[PDB]
Length: 293
Ligand SMILES: CCCCCCCCCCCCCCCCCC(=O)O
Image 1: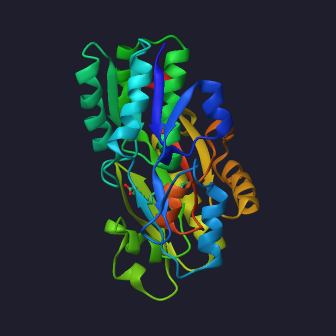
Image 2: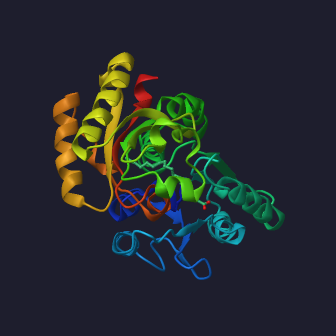
């Protein structure tokens, strides 16, 4: 029996965490740059979105989890004899992974025969949730840790997020915009269609109208799924401030792609991503079914 751990960027539902025994190590958010609140623990996802929606000039800051936060979780499981597997947001967005690496080392000092595996998921939000869920599936289906790890690279390489946001303001201010900043996207009124793959974000298209942008998101995903064998993928949706739009989007996804969503890994996009996307991200994530690899 493994104790699966993730940082809070994965956005897995309360229900999922209880059902599959996944433990979350929270990132923090600050609105004034002085006081920080642990994601989901000291503040709720809905409250954070509200602060941003109420104040379009407010740019909050995120902070990686402390080494001690990871260490206390690792330690409590390890002294019970549990092997630990810990997933983090992509190292290209956050130093979360390296906090966990330092925390593993800390715990080893006091428990030299401890089994702790730290994984740079190379994902975020929906695809981090999809990857964790593939791992949860493999272990529940009776694969050994080694058998599951032998599929990890291919799973991570196959993951994609296809999404759009309300503006470039938060991405630029938060420093992770990277290749999504171009001459075209810098023009007044334009929003990007964004693709997350291989641990980072890139530009998949542009537009101006919310509904047209969501249609472009779907067309970009459809091309990828068609190329790679749609039947062999799990598909889930992530939504931001407007839950109704999210549910309606899920219908468009199922209709356009001719799939049924895996609802367990649908996510209300969390604070970690929202601080950087703004309160209006919407999109879908996909990942290969391990069985097909
Ligand atoms: C369907 C899901 C759509 C939302 C996808 C958003 C994923 C990529 C957007 C960029 C996210 C940057 C997050 C950086 C978090 C930094 C945390 C920290 O301070 O260490």
